[PDB]
């Protein structure tokens, strides 16, 4: 049902995908089955979500029942930064691929640019809650990830939560084999990412917008925090099209050629979230939405600026 954004590899990445962070076991399998039924072909996964085994089961079912073919699915996962040491990249990946019950991933991403203390404690922190770093860097990880592409286990690599400085650091690495095909970052009307999107596109890098609905269920949300779904100015535009706020928030990215990955385990909403190809936001509506930028991050809670390669303090 989705249109696509063409990658530099010429592969076609479906422009709407299904997010899976915080999708509980017992619900994420049904969420994936409903999404594939509703036309979704892009599923966004990660090691750290600890639910890939259930996503894998759902994907397998639907393949078994002729609902869809593997080659028409676009499956993305992410390498967590406790596994940046070369040998751990492979092991972490093997776990992700075994859990997803697949023979290859369409895209494998660096989840976050800063290396953490290596190993299977996923959230190494000091007594205050500050991240504990490791010596292996995202360039060390990328080296190991490039092997996976050589071997055909992964069709393309990308990054997530990179600023243009980290992308430059990657693109400018001498001896680079594969370039990233996408940069997955938070993006919505309160964080429009104009300069970052401009930069990525100019380098042949697509952008995938995460938390496009402002992630209203994030555990750290405070009642005073901005709420996109309840924003009267967003709802105004949705009303004009007899659509929902969520549909507007999703359509916003599609019209910027930015891939978008809203999360839901609610069947009605999973369906709602992909009914975004039967309307168009006007230029005036797009301009108004863009004007809502307040450089605001729903995902900005973690304490890690004390380590090298912190992405969020640069201008873009
Ligand atoms: N790379 C990264 O660092 C990173 C960071 C954050 C997220 N992500 C990815 O991006 C995905 C999406 O971001 P997100 O999960 O933070 O938040 P989000 O997609 O902006 O919002 C998800 C929340 O909105 C609800 N929802 C979904 N559709 C709705 C609708 N039509 N109307 C009202 N509410 C709706 C969902 O509820 P129900 O599920 O209960 O329906 C869920 O509580 C994640 O799942 C993950 O795959 C990546
Ligand atoms: O994980 C949970 O169930 C709840 O965890 C929290 C709840 C609150 Cl209110 C604040 C912070 C956390 C937290 O730091 N979690 C570890 C944690 C991350 F650090 C991270 F970056 C990713 Br991505 C994760 F997936 C992940 F789980
Ligand atoms: O990744 C997802 O899909 C969900 O994201 C989260 C979930 C939880 Cl429980 C806690 C934090 C996040 C989150 O902030 N993630 C982006 C992210 C990191 F991953 C990270 F390691 C550092 Br450090 C960051 F500062 C940060 F911004």
Image (cartoon, rainbow, N blue to C red):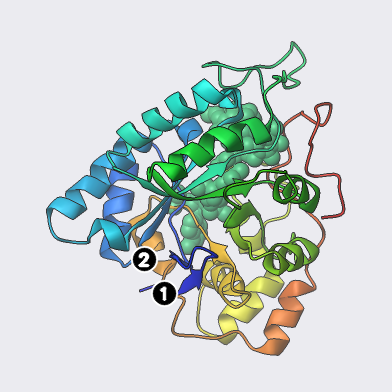
244 sits to left or right of 179 = left
Q: Residues within 10 Å of mark 1 (few under 14, many from 20)?
A: some
**Circle number at residue 275:** 1
Q: Residue furthest front?
A: 175
Direction from residue 66 to residue 75 in the image, left or right: right
The disc label shown at residue 314, or none:
none
Query: Residue 271 got which mark?
Result: 2
Q: Of all residues shown, which one is farthest toward the left?
A: 65
Identify the image quadrant of residue 214: bottom right
Pick whichever, 81 or 191, lies toward us.
Answer: 81
**43 up-or-down from 98: above or below:** below
Percent of width and height locating residue 46 = 47, 39
Residue 239 versus residue 206 in the image, above or below: below
Q: Residue at x 28, y 48 (%)?
A: 30
Q: What residue occupies the far top of the structure in this picture?
A: 127
Q: Position of residue 12 (x, y in %)?
A: 44, 67
Q: Is residue 210 visible?
A: no
- Residue 203 pos. (x, y %): 70, 64
Residue closer to the observer: 56 or 94:
94
The response on whether ligand 1 sits within 8 Å of label 2 is no
- SS for dot 2: helix
Specify whether residue 273 is in view: yes
Query: CB of mark 1 within 8 Å of CB of mark 2?
Result: yes
Density class for disc 2 (Cα within 10 Å; few <14, some 14-19, many ≥20) is some
Q: Quadrant of residue 192?
A: bottom right
Q: Nearer the viewer, residue 20 or 272?
A: 20
Judge: label 1 CB < 8 Å from ligand 1.
no
Residue sitting at x 18%, y 61% = 67
């Amino acid at each position: 049902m989705a249109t696509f954004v063409e990658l530099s590899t010429k592969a076609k990445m479906p422009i709407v995908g299904l997010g899976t962070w915080k999708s509980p076991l017992g619900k994420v399998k049904e969420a994936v089955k409903v999404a594939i039924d509703a036309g979704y072909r892009h599923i966004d996964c990660a090691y750290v979500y600890q639910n890939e085994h259930e996503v894998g089961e759902a994907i397998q079912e639907k393949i078994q029942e002729k609902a869809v073919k593997r080659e028409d699915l676009f499956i993305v996962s992410k390498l967590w930064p406790t596994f940046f040491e070369r040998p751990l990249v492979r092991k972490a990946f093997e776990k992700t691929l075994k859990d997803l019950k697949l023979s290859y991933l369409d895209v494998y991403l660096i989840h976050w640019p800063q290396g953490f203390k290596s190993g299977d404690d996923l959230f190494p922190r000091d007594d205050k809650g500050n991240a504990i770093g490791g010596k292996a860097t995202f360039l060390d990880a990328w080296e190991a990830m490039e092997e996976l592409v050589d071997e055909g286990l992964v069709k393309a690599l990308g990054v997530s939560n990179f600023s243009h400085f980290q992308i430059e650091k990657l693109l400018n690495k001498p001896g680079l084999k594969y370039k990233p095909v996408t940069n997955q970052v938070e993006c919505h009307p309160y964080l429009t990412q104009e300069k970052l999107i401009q930069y990525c596109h100019s380098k042949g890098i697509t952008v995938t917008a995460y938390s496009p609905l402002g992630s209203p269920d994030r555990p750290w949300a405070k009642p005073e925090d901005p709420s996109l779904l309840e924003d009267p100015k967003i709802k105004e535009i949705a009303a004009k099209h007899k659509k929902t706020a969520a549909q507007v928030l999703i359509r916003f990215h599609i019209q910027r050629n930015v891939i978008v990955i809203p999360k839901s385990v609610t069947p009605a909403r999973i369906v709602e979230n992909i009914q975004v190809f039967d309307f168009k936001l006007s230029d005036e509506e797009m301009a108004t939405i863009l004007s809502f930028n307040r450089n605001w991050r729903a995902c900005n809670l973690l304490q890690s600026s004390h380590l090298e390669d912190y992405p969020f303090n640069a201008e873009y």
